[PDB]
Length: 272
Image (cartoon, rainbow, N blue to C red; front, side, top):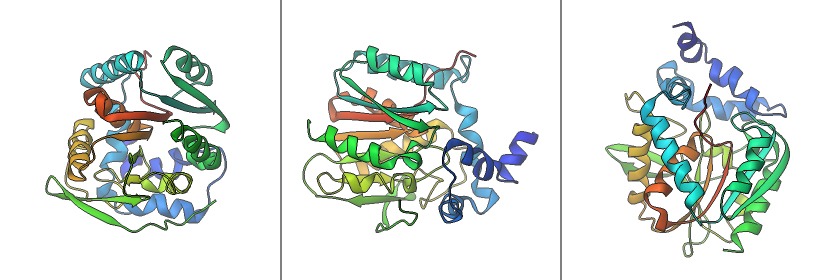
């Protein structure tokens, strides 16, 4: 497979596909932070498995059914929702995003303007502040955060933990091919009032990277165990890309524990 050779050996997903998910040009110091987890090609299996797990034309059936179920849940749920989107987008066209805010119950839409997939890198000030104005009702290239580590299923996962200890914590779930680094400029707009937790997915960021196939079920197992390892009860979700698949799948299974979902460029079944 030549496609797999480019993603694994030539790192095309990091050096090519990821810059095509941001409208503005990144800097070499920002790209160094996205490169650092995947310096060794043997650590790049998540970069290849994630797009091969996308729900496209009814395959893979296990993902398509899972995503259909939480999309069905989201349309039935009264949980407050906040939907960011940009033009032209990547996973969500601007027309389908605005139509989704109509159909979803209790959903506020936010036009961010210019955006592809990494809307956090194009306009982190609108996203972080509109989240803060939303939680009330209920640029930096470094990573200035203390590394917290918790043992999960025999492996060790890294996460960001800032903000007050009381109240409802806010769980930030990144996607492919990022890490908690993608929330570095959103978190400061929320940390002064609400606890902010931003884990790195297993095999990504600073978390441990075992010899796994890194299917979606692998992330589900590790993210379920992460949330119980931290002792989180009720949470607010801020989810993006494949993190939205984890966030929505966990919210569908534990709807009484979710107080609000802010999402953008999320996972949905694609007919063609």
